[PDB]
Image 1 (cartoon, chains in turn brown, green, purple):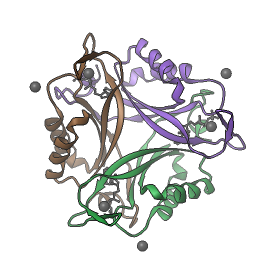
Image 2 (spheres, chains in turn blue, cyan, purple):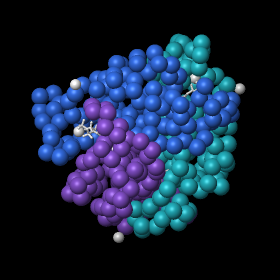
Image 3 (cartoon, protein in one colour):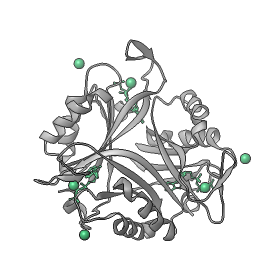
Image 4 (tube, helix red, strand yellow):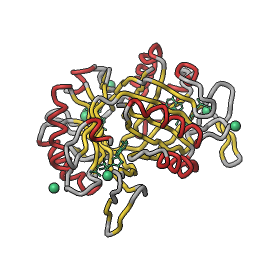
Length: 113
Length: 113
Length: 113
Ligand SMILES: Nc1ncnc2c1ncn2[C@@H]1O[C@H](COP(=O)(O)OP(=O)(O)OP(=O)(O)O)[C@@H](O)[C@H]1O
Ligand SMILES: Nc1ncnc2c1ncn2[C@@H]1O[C@H](COP(=O)(O)OP(=O)(O)OP(=O)(O)O)[C@@H](O)[C@H]1O
Ligand SMILES: Nc1ncnc2c1ncn2[C@@H]1O[C@H](COP(=O)(O)OP(=O)(O)OP(=O)(O)O)[C@@H](O)[C@H]1O
Ligand SMILES: [Cl-]
Ligand SMILES: [Cl-]
Ligand SMILES: [Cl-]
Ligand SMILES: [Mg+2]
Ligand SMILES: [Mg+2]
Ligand SMILES: [Mg+2]
């Protein structure tokens, strides 16, 4: 099992969300964050101004899936979230040792099906 | 060391929190999130309406503990957070390689005691 | 690759942020959380009152770096965030299996450079 954490542009939420639902994702969590991602020598454009290290609003998507579904999920997010301008986002994949469904106590594969 | 991340119903915060404090948990983090968890063919009830993939408000609890305490923490959350209606929540356990207490620089077991 | 998650006092954001930018960090994410950290028998001071398990506002910083940069990042956060009063914060380091830059599809070391 893996956790996929994707930082995306806020306006992209709808476009990304539809891609994931159509791909068969059945659970996801979203939160509001702020961030910077300043590659060397670049500025990020937002509403007609250029930024270096100021924090900009982003959204964090969290999706826990079976290992065999990670690449599909990654591909769907990338294709829907990208624009070609710096600031499009970043995805981090991390291990999940156990998953538990609260209502039933189901575990692991059963809790993500 | 493990991180326990629990997504719960917002109203349950107090009921869950009291269970964990009584069990001896000494540190926890809470954040506001939104989410869906649509098992196939189901709808989630909220304030008299039925939802499919709309995002609903949830809370994310994060608790870092020693390995030997994980199952106790899981049990306390499940028992306090559940209601029997879909939407009760989900728990993800993940590895923590190092913990550092900022004030003192204490590490690992010392930083979670 | 590792994720560094640091819970800090909200007022410290600026002091911590400047330390990390000067150390060469190029990406970070911040979120608003609440928390308690009650070591046995202690109270946390906030705006002239003493707290046990009430939730206090904190900030969560998330920084994904190469393994060889973790200790530098940890040191910079600790030195900038600390005050000597309980409630200064806690840092959790966890594994990241894959990183993807959304705009380009670059992976891993390429996505964090
Ligand atoms: N290494 C990192 N650790 C934590 N958060 C990061 C990191 N890099 C980026 N982020 C988060 O992702 C957001 C988007 O980053 P961004 O798209 O600018 O990445 P980038 O590597 O600079 O790529 P690009 O060249 O496309 O801008 C940031 O604002 C921040 O919230
Ligand atoms: N696989 C997942 N990845 C990330 N977040 C998830 C996932 N599944 C659920 N969540 C989060 O947990 C919340 C509660 O999920 P929920 O209780 O609906 O899970 P479920 O598996 O559908 O179980 P139930 O049948 O009890 O509804 C969601 O709204 C979402 O925030
Ligand atoms: N084990 C933990 N799991 C999750 N979050 C924690 C944990 N311990 C602390 N936190 C988070 O970090 C914040 C700061 O904790 P705090 O500085 O009080 O830690 P502490 O171990 O009690 O150290 P101190 O003695 O310096 O107070 C908390 O309010 C909470 O948000
Ligand atoms: Cl493009
Ligand atoms: Cl029931
Ligand atoms: Cl001091
Ligand atoms: Mg960038
Ligand atoms: Mg559900
Ligand atoms: Mg404390």
